[PDB]
Amino acid sequence: MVHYYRLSLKSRQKAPKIVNSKYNSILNIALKNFRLCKKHKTKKPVQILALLQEIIPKSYFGTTTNLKRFYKVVEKILTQSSFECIHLSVLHKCYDYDAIPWLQNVEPNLRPKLLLKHNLFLLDNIVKPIIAFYYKPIKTLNGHEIKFIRKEEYISFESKVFHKLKKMKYLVEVQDEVKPRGVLNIIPKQDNFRAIVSIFPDSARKPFFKLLTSKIYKVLEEKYKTSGSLYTCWSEFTQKTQGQIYGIKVDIRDAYGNVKIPVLCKLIQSIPTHLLDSEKKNFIVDHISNQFVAFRRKIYKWNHGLLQGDPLSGCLCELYMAFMDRLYFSNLDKDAFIHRTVDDYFFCSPHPHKVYDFELLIKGVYQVNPTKTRTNLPTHRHPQDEIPYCGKIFNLTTRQVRTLYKLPPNYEIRHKFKLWNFNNQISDDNPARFLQKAMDFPFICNSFTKFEFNTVFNDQRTVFANFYDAMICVAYKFDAAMMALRTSFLVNDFGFIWLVLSSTVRAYASRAFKKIVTYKGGKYRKVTFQCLKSIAWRAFLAVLKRRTEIYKGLIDRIKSREKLTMKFHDGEVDASYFCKLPEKFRFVKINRKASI
Image 1 (cartoon, rainbow, N blue to C red):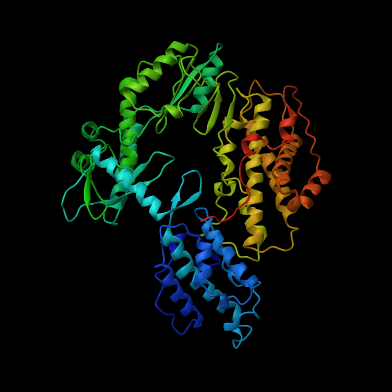
Image 2: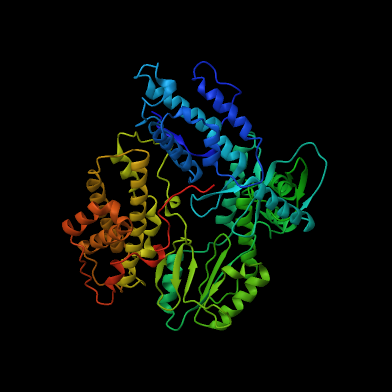
């Protein structure tokens, strides 16, 4: 029932000095050379795919081919995404079982499962462990992307930051033998840093912290106002506002850290006993003012707002932010547009001076990241009609809204996906069910919301563009899943693609249609089903042309068996946008390769 092998570096085991009788004696030599490699180590740069060559003797694989078949799995671990795994079958399938010495006087039928048991050993005892020995995995937060930084370079950074936390008195040394509550790490967010703690933890406080987290979220929806509906706010604003819309999007800096601990406590107190009694009066208040952390075998005290990674910080921030929000954000123009989230405000107005002033107030009440501030004020140096907010792009002039796709240059588009699910594992002999799950709706469901397919304020062309761009994402995952099929599944007969892909195209054009209808508007003209369908096909072709040598057959089938020509019943819609890969997606990498 279990076919997946997690590429995650978190499965590595403490390698033994020698293997027992269940393993061939070859592995002993390997384990031995391994121990030697962990000593010759120098701060000098190494490549895991080269040390293993010194560790696992070639006498193990027999022929270069078998050696290469395996070291591919290593490269997968070296260039993995969070949640990625392969089929255990790939560890024993195809291998030239004759060229393998230690498996000769072993019955030809018992060989598959034996090689599996061994390749796994190496992977879990040497390969993964030596990777983690030199490097440190870091989740970049931009999807399931993972970067491997040399432990030396990471530690050096961790220190630079650690001392900064000392001098700025965000940490203070103590002497207690207990109460750390957790250990703090330093994740290199972009180019700044983010200091976070980790609960030890204990299950004797977890169903308790849940009741608290939930109870505080209740105080929010019962005592404090909501930001309202983004779709509604932007709808009504554009409906009534006829002049030039002016707006600013500000990003609050260190929301968790800029919390005034003294005040948040007094906020927890004033909470009506209806919800939360004298238990919060002390505990939640106590927890906040007493956030101790364990670092380098020393327990420093954090006194800079709330700590990230603390089970309480999540809700307490939303309570403190909604409190502040209520203090200095009451008297905003009632005819103006306002919208807040985690740490992002979005103020619009036909009167620029009011937008101008909102920023001043917002910079007075909070601290902001100016580099992430987006506006169209003349007073700013980089005006833009298009400001990003809540995964959508609002054009202050055309009033149009498009999905926000965070795709940095050179970013590997595959990471954006979670093709492998460890709870619902798909056997290697069934590629159809795998390709299907990949082509589901759940993931791109965000690009299929009112914001994209509404016709109240969005032009006919914008809706078609929103669909095309979202289908490109799908199309990009199709290629991403197709790679997995020929690497893990080891598919040779590529024919079932047509059944899934054709169903995928039709299914989505329908998803669009129904959505375009549910949110029709005065900007509507006519969205013919066959048109939506064409865009979907136009999308797959755009992403597919990136591997003309691989998808040659698939492309031709689309160009001949499908009517790609779409009939926009609307005139003000440039159709040439669907005849090429959108520039937004023109910079993603679709070519994997190990480097570390």
